[PDB]
Amino acid sequence: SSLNQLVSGLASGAVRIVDLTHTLDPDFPVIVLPPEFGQCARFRMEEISAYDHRGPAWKWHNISMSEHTGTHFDAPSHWISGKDVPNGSVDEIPAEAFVGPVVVIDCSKGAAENDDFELTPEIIAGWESEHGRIPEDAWVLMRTDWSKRRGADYLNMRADGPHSPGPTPEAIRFLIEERNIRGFGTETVGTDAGQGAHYVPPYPAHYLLHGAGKYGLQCLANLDQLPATGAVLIAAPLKIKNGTGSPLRVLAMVT
Amino acid sequence: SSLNQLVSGLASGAVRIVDLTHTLDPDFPVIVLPPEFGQCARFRMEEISAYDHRGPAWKWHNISMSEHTGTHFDAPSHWISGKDVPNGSVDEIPAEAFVGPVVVIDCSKGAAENDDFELTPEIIAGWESEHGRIPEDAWVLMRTDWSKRRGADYLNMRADGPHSPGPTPEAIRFLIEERNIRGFGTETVGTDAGQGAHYVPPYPAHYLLHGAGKYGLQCLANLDQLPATGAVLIAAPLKIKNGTGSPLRVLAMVT
Ligand SMILES: Nc1ccccc1C(=O)C(=O)O
Ligand SMILES: Nc1ccccc1C(=O)C(=O)O
Ligand SMILES: [Mn+2]
Ligand SMILES: [Mn+2]
């Protein structure tokens, strides 16, 4: 069966697993919004005990964060457009959605030349002419190697806001309506471009994806280790009651 | 090759995904220790905004918990015996450890008759005469249907402590030394019996497993939906810096 052969492949090294997740720690940046809005929290952790009088033979921590901290998954209820879609929270999404085919569109050269680099319908058509049509219900990842930027360069906040690559409304509408993708993922802090508030509609990845009951992934790492096609993405969010998303361990299995 | 067949199976339903995770919520019980010690925290969440003046077009929460809250994963560094094993924290465990073969030993009839039901080497031997030798580097799950218990029955706290099924020290030692398992999982709050403090060594699942650089899973649900052999477990914990474990979405793929 396919499961027995996956086990054999993982055992022999014919199938490798790539970790697409940033480490959770207090220093990792989270999305920054205008100061009048409630803000996403950074990851924090505190010891309960560390093999001491509070717990002599064990070590463990309390942790705090937001649903949208670090490498994380966005459910449709995250956006106003996904308010009434079925199974809109992370605890309600059907489990078969958490494992599936993934395609990677390499936009890293574009991002290196332009902070606001745009994934367009034209780029998608060019990619498909080379790698074949995007299969239905696939995860689509926009590779930018943005995960290599550290410090203030990662959010890349300027006076007129953050500047980081992302999809145009037309690119997202195409993926949803013409390809019925499962979800869209980025190496940036958001599924939308840094300047994405200024598209029509505002935050089109969030508005259109979540309005269609589709999912988002953000702050992905190591996309440069993945093939354009043929890998399998594992992205199972925490089963948070009525959760709009959660941090998660994103993995890719590759041949 | 094998991944293409997995994709095909997942798409067609020839491969099904079983969700083994309890919902993360304030009311799900966590392990309780003697009062002089630091205690595991319950899951908590608060709204940042809900499509309102705090965040007009979006909804999201801040969340807090322990590494060992709910359906969760225990890394070797959790126990004093595994403090110094290489790759001992959840952020260091090789990603290939997160996907692999799983066997399910059905102890539900026993658990229904005895709150303190013990998984023994003899029971494991009986399981193997029926289902074949436990494969090396496999996840072993102790099924008890304990997850069907709600209210105070789940912790099953009495005047002399909690009473819930678990493995004997000899069982764990056998699985480690004679079968070289990857890890051990249960539907109860701990990988150890409720009365596991009174074994030698105290809490032997933790002491022995984590001492051997092996992993734990706790509070699993729906084990009664899995085959004894043939399934693949997906158990990828959060990439917490120096983390001793984390809540996670545990899944099984079944043919
Ligand atoms: N929470 C948000 C609010 C406004 C704009 C964007 C976002 C995100 O990118 C997010 O989902 O983390
Ligand atoms: N953290 C503990 C401390 C003492 C005994 C048991 C435990 C656990 O079961 C656990 O790892 O969740
Ligand atoms: Mn998000
Ligand atoms: Mn634990």
Image (spheres, coloured by chain):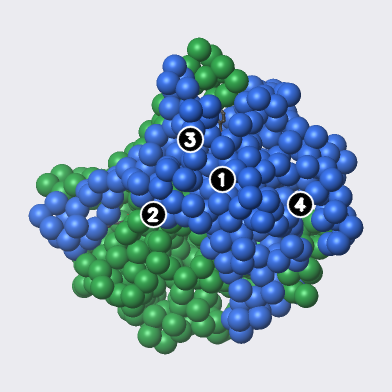
Chain colours: A blue, B green
Amino acid carrying label 1: it is Thr
How far from the left and from the top, in percent, is residue A185?
A: 64, 47
Same-subunit check for callouts 4 and 1:
yes
Q: For the point 71% across and 66% down, which residue is it?
A: A227
Q: Amino acid at mark 4?
A: Ala
- Marked residue chain, label 3: A
Mark in front: 4 vs 3: 3
**In the rendered view of the protein, which quadrant contains the C terminus of chain B?**
bottom right
Amino acid carrying mark 3 in the image: Met
Does any atom of ligand 1 lie closer than 8 Å to the CB of label 1?
Answer: no
Q: Earlier in the sequence, mark 4 or mark 3?
A: 4
**Quadrant of the image for the N terminus of chain B?**
bottom right
Chain letter for the residue marked with disc 2 in the picture: B
**Badge number at residue B240:** 2
Numbered label attached to residue A138:
4
Q: Nearer the viewer, residue A250 or A88?
A: A250
Task: Specify the label residue A188 is tagged with.
Answer: 1
**Residue A188 in picture, x, y percent from top left:** 56, 45
Q: Which residue is mark 3?
A: A157
Label 3 to label 1: alpha-carbon separation: 13 Å
Q: In this rendering, does residue B228 appear at all?
A: no
Residue displayed at 58% across by 56% down: A145
The local crowd at label 4, few if under 14, some if 14 to 19, many if 20 or more residues have their Cα within 10 Å, is many
Image quadrant where residue A180 sits? top right
Figure check: B61 above or below B156: above
Q: Nearer the viewer, mark 4 or mark 1?
A: 1
Residue pictured at 42% horizontal, 87% vertical: B178
